[PDB]
Amino acid sequence: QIPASEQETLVRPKPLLLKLLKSVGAQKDTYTMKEVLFYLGQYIMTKRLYDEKQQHIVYCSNDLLGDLFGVPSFSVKEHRKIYTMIYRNLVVV
Ligand SMILES: CC[C@@H](CS(=O)(=O)C(C)(C)C)N1C(=O)[C@@](C)(CC(=O)O)C[C@H](c2cccc(Cl)c2)[C@H]1c1ccc(Cl)cc1
């Protein structure tokens, strides 16, 4: 459904997203989506907003991530929706 070439595209996170990304990776002016997805994913795991015990759902209503995505929770398996939420927070280069 989602082509792998999409992970090579270049983007610039908006201020709030950049704040989240910097807690897990070095600050950069331009990121590849592969980088954005990893840092976002790593932020979710280190903060345990995703417990492998709780059937694929990430709970973020008590986190900045919830403010970024505009939702209290979401499934890690519904990738199309994740991309749409992430793009609301970045600008394509
Ligand atoms: C928070 C969970 C992270 C950890 S992880 O792999 O990124 C890693 C362990 C490498 C940090 N994560 C996953 O667990 C995965 C394996 C969940 C799944 O599809 O079964 C993949 C997921 C992912 C990867 C690429 C693109 C999308 Cl939209 C989602 C990806 C993910 C990345 C960002 C967001 Cl916002 C949501 C889910």
Image: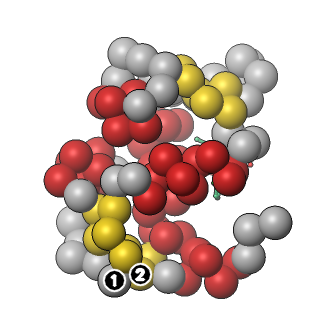
Above or below — where is 6 with respect to 37?
A: below
Drawn side of residue 75 relative to residue 50, left or right? right
Image x and y of residue 87, in percent: 44, 58
> Which numbered marker is on residue 93?
1
Tell whether 52 sits left or right of 64: right
Q: Kindly identify which residue carries mark 2.
A: 10
Observer-nearest of 42 and 69: 69
Q: Specify the amino acid type for callout 2.
A: Leu
Compared across the picture, whether 76 is left or right of 41 comes to right
Q: The residue tagged with tag 1: helix, strand or loop?
A: loop
Evaluate if marks 1 and 2 touch, with contact meaning CB atoms under 8 Å apart. Answer: yes
Residue 40 locus on image (x, y percent): 45, 50
**At 68% across and 33% down in the image, what residue appears?**
75
Look at discs 1 and 2 and give the one toward the viewer. Answer: 1
Q: Residue at x 48, y 26 (%)?
A: 71
Q: Is 20 placed left or right of 36 in the picture?
A: left
What amino acid is labelled 1 in the image?
Val
Tell me how far mark 1 sits from mark 2, CA to CA. Answer: 5 Å
Crowd around label 2: few <14 · some 14–19 · many ≥20 (10 Å): some
Image quadrant containing the N terminus: bottom right
Residue 12 location (% of width, % of height) = 29, 71
x and y, in percent, of residue 26 in the image: 25, 65
**Is the residue indicated by label 1 positioned so its CB lies within 8 Å of ligand 1?**
no
Does residue 40 show up? yes
Residue at 43 percent across and 37 percent down: it is: 69
